[PDB]
Image (cartoon, rainbow, N blue to C red; front, side):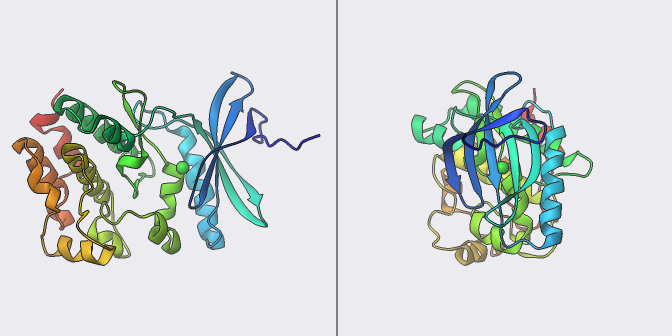
Length: 273
Ligand SMILES: [Cl-]
């Protein structure tokens, strides 16, 4: 008999089918044996966490189960197990197979202005939802590659919330952090939800320009110099819509105190609906 893995409740079953593999995370196809709907069985492990960091990892993953929002990926279950002699986190999520904003831009080359306005508003809705939880949830790792879509003319859903919690730790932040999207205060000890606004601005810039922000830079230190010197990414001057350009500028300001808030963005006339 083959050993088949299950959730502690027995509801979710793991397939021996690997869907994706990255740092700290391997995604397998799974099955809800009660509804007979296929899911994503995500196994997370950061072997360099301390005991207190792993425990916080376990607790933050378990809080994802209670999240229910149209623009957040659905996280059905979570528990702590062991993998290769050390603890790991399993995270069962809805199966996203329709691509991301990244694969969307690579497929359709450019994003039409009405699509950008609609999907950017939905990202702000999801971030507003995360920021108003108890305790508040900071994404810390928002990028076009982890904003999933339900279809070419569907909705967006913020994902990879389990992996994103590892940005709070040293080793993982240097491995999975995308410096082009990270606000400058993320290289300090303490920061707040304004880093999600900064990353949102870079997502909006990438959507508005169909290119990688700060692609002209070679490493994080180069980007950090430009950001802290008030030097915008070169793609910023390719934004054709002056209203979109004004919103991006307000989101990627180097000083957090001058940065626009989520409430300011949703109350902006561009996102009025
Ligand atoms: Cl995740």
